[PDB]
Each structure stands twice: as structure tokens, then as C-alpha cells.
Image (cartoon, rainbow, N blue to C red):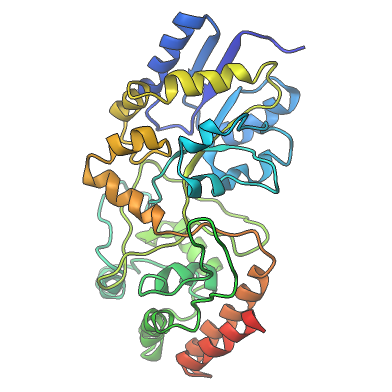
Length: 370
């Protein structure tokens, strides 16, 4: 039997914890149910080490990515007790937290934007992808390269060309198919031939992969770097970053990786999970509570439609929200293997000049429909 009458809140660190504290001050003053609030920087390993004994926090806040294993381990409790709370949110944001049949977490915020930089807190982000090769030679003229990455794989090169118009699979406002593959589309080749244009002249590092890029960033040489998707079956080197940064795009067109939104889950070890669910839908999710956390730090768009319109009163929010609306969610289909295996060969074919971009694309799209 667990300790009844209490709740604990752990956050990522560097977040607007001071604004969130007040929400818990109000609720605990009205209900008496304890509310602790902490701003740790190692909770990602502590949460699964304490909650495993039923002694960890009662609530957790992280992107769905890190939740890909916590629910399987039994740490995340079943959420969505009824259907009313679902209508309070947009449908896409629910898909962004799904599991096989059952549910494991719920959407909180909608800010899909981050970018990594050198060990020096000098804010000088790139203006566009076409400036990278232009700045690379200028920094090399006084030291080393500007930006480096795993150009050798499709996972990181997908968000490049998708800006011109390429897309993996179509996903309407709740209807999905795998038949509509935007691989063999002019936009894919358009952005892809830019990469190859540099390699053509050998001015660009055509031999840089994950290993080369990762290492150089660890050394502190690369003035900037990119991270995010998981190509390999495991990661051996993990980077970290405080706050937010802008993200460069293509010539007159924004980029679109995946719809990465903020989520929350209830700990399954608590005695009465209702205490947590109630606090969330009584004081956190209010025009006063959400405002308090947003006052302490900018949180951008929200999953809660009722307050979405309020934050949407400013363009910084609205535009960032539209980027998630027009975006796609990473699927859970087996077809991804065929897709990854196919596109990999098409990029190598263009990079090696073994085949025309146009034809390698045609071939590749066929490998996904055959």
C-alpha cells in the first residue's frame, strides 16, 4: 500500500518551474493533497529507477519519444477515463501519444522546433541551408567547418528534400494509407540534387558520416550540428541542449521532419491516479494556470483547444501551431523497413553518380509499392 494524499512533479530542467509551482500551491491549499515540484537534470534515469519500486514521481512530462519504453515497462498508467477530455484536444495530438489499442499518455503542448550548437553560448544560427556551404568555406578559411552531419543516410536527409515538397506517406486528418508515396516526386529530387551538386565539385565533405560528424562535434570543432531521428537500432552517443533555437529551411520553403509534441503520463504505482488526473484537469489546464507557466517561460501552442486560441492570439504561436497541423506523425508500420532500405540506395546512387536522381527515385518508390 502506497502513501495516499500526495503528488510529485518532475520537469526536464531549465523549464518554467516557478510558474508551474503556483498551480500546485493553489490546488494543495484547496485540497491538501501534497504537491512537490522539482527542476532536476537527471530525472530521465532517476524516474525509471525510483518508480520501478513504486517510490518515484506521480506524474511525468516528456516527448512521446522517451515514452516509447516507459509504458512497456509498466511505469505509465492507462489514461483517458472518458471521451470528453479527448474532445478538449485536437485529433492529431492524440495519435502522437498512441500505443497498440490502449493509451499511455496525453498531449500537452505543440512546439516542434529545436537546433543544437557548439559548446559556446554564442547565438549565431544559420539563415538557410544554402548558406551552410557558403559559411563552411569562410570558417574553414580561419579554422574549421561550420556544420557536419550523416549525409550518408536517408533519416537525416529526409527533412532536407521534404521542404521542396517530398513526403514519406500521406496521412489525412485521421485516414492513413501507404499507397501514396511522395518519393518519386520532383520536390524530392529538387532538394536532393543540391547535396549532390556540392559533392560533384568535391568541395563538400562527401565522406562524412555519423561517426565523423558525431566525433567532430564532441571535439568542439563543428560550430553547429543536428540530431533527432533514430536510424541505427541503438544510440551510443547522446547530445543535450538548453532552451530553444530556430531551424534553417530550404530556398523559399520551410522544413517538416515529424510532429514532435510535448506529452504527459500518470505513474501507474500511485494509489489513486485520480488525484493526478483531477489536478491536471482542474488547475493546470485553466486560463490562469496555463498562463502562469507561460509567464515564467514561453511554451508556445497548447494541445488544449480551449486555450489554444488564447495563445494563438500572437503569430509566434499560430505559425508554430500550423507547422504541426500541416505535419506528419512517424508511423508504426513494418513498411518503414522497405522505405528506409529503398531511399538509402537512391541517395547513394545519386551521390556516386551511378544513376540519375529522377530514375533512382522512380526505382525507390517502386520498391515501396511492389
